[PDB]
Amino acid sequence: LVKNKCVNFNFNGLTGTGVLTESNKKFLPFQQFGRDIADTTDAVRDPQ
Amino acid sequence: KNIDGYFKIYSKHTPINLVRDLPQGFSALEPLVDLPIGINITRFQTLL
Image 1 (tube, rainbow over the protein chains, first blue to last red):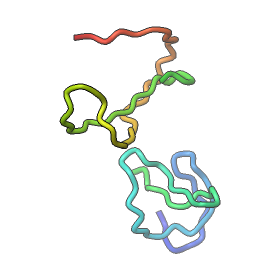
Image 2: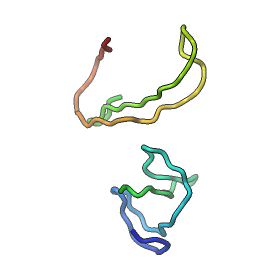
Image 3: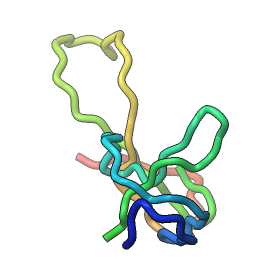
Image 4: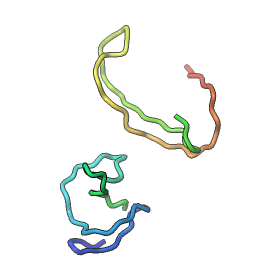
């Protein structure tokens, strides 16, 4: 895992390309993604 | 509910006090499980 640096990625088959940072977005135990008003993948949780 | 090989469950365990009926108040049900079984289910029965 790399941070603060533009990377391609795939998580768990979720893909996309972004800048993965550290975020205080309290997720849920079963929660996988985050999303956003525009319906655009936002936060994720590192599967491992 | 059964969709696409998936029976699915959700749950809540909540304290109440009413003897008669479903308390009036809102809380919603995270999944526990998914079972990739592939049965077809038209009926069911509880057990005691």
